[PDB]
Amino acid sequence: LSKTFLNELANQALTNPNDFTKGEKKQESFLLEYVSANPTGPLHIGHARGAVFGDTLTRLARHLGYKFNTEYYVNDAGNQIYLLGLSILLSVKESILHENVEYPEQYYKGEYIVDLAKEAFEKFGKEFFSEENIPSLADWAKDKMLVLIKQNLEQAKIKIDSYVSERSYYDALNATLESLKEHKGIYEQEGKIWLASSQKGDEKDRVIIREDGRGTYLAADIVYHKDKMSRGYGKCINIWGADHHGYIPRMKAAMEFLGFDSNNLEIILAQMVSLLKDGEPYKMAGNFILMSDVVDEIGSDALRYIFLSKKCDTHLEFDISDLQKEDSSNPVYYINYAHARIHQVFAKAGKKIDDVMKADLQSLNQDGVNLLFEALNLKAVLNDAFEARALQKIPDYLKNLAANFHKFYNENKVVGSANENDLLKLFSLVALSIKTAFSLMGIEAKNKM
């Protein structure tokens, strides 16, 4: 490899560190809709992989110069959020008002439900709490839960750019039906309006409008997707749970019956995650494991690492006891340790990264040149990771780069040596790749351990 050439690349990277590996403005634009959990509680742990994957995808797309929007769909219909209003009323009655109450077979319970009930009782007063005020309670509640969900996401360094309401699509149903008919996608049978999805590769035809006159969940989903796909984006991306694979053909069929090319709807499937502690499955104030509880225990960086660390449609198993170790087996520690080790050697040498810029890297041994190449190779990795949707290439890159750095620095004396500046400049570039790649994972690199 040409050290002269790589040194020039090193100089370009280090002169404008914030622009290192950033791509020029791209032509293809995207709309990602992800997470989209019901506003009826805090995020469960099963939402974490989709959330972590989507935010990393977003950060990566933006870094590479793609126009990339994010959106969350709020299932906030009165009929959807009624049970949440019901459940708060019931826990006001039993935990605050102390009466014996009838409980249905499906209801929301937990520490969050009793805290919100205490918030409800303080805001509305005792008088309010009757069956007629349930949807007034549910509206207030679902807004509080959406605030909760937003901060659940913020805890994991995730912000979504647009939250959209189901309720704002009640007027949009007719235009969907019409557009579907204009492509011969709908028909009446047995008092119901059906989508002819089996004419477009689905297993069987599907109900759009019930005999009741009401739209189905599928109808609502089609309406929303019609809006998303007619917004001018190059592609719409969804992240769905892997158990929703059978739902793909009916949605593609619907999009074809709306005049859209269904290849412009990309479905990414997020597979199940197994969390372990001490070899046993993770467990514990609720019947579900909360994303919040896991972030409380392991921290944000660990969540952002673990949930990105294996191919999205493959099963991920991780033991959280590994985060107690301070070696190769705790990759967040180990990668951060590489970055911190560089920061410390610069302090030991009494130098800033601008003092070593003038070095030309010509004295680097083969191990140093490999590490230099590896540092600069981030650009290739990031572009490849985006285009293949293989985000686990980012942790993989970082793992190997930290390993190789650590091994290099163990075997090479720096401060006081005749090529101190060459080695420091090398190190400054390794630190930059660690910091850059980590930031796209929503992790800030540590200067000190």
Image (cartoon, helix red, strand yellow):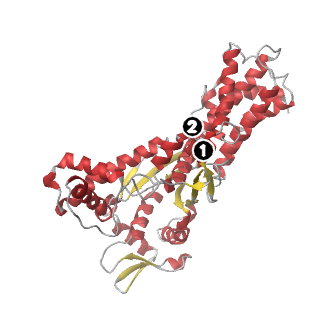
418 left or right, relative to 285: right
Most extreme residue toward the bottom, as rendered? 190
Residue 379 rendering spot, x and y as whole percentages:
69, 39
Residue 7 picture location, percent across and down:
78, 26
Q: Does residue 21 show up? A: no
Which class describes the residues within 10 Å of circle 2: few (<14), some (14-19), or many (20+)? many
Residue at 48%, 71% (x, y): give it.
257
The image quarter in which residue 364 lies: top right
Mark 1 burial class by Cα count in 10 Å: few <14, some 14-19, many 20+: many
Rendered-image quadrant of the C terminus: top right
Seen at 21% across and 49% down, the residue is 121
Sooner in the amino-acid sequence: mark 1 or mark 2: 1
Q: Position of residue 304 (x, y in %)?
A: 56, 44
Q: What amino acid type is highlighted by mark number 1? A: Tyr
- Marks 1,2: beta carbons within 8 A: yes
Residue bearing the label numbered 1 = 305
Give 101 or 214, whichever is nearer the viewer: 101
Q: List the residue tagged with mark 2.
A: 443
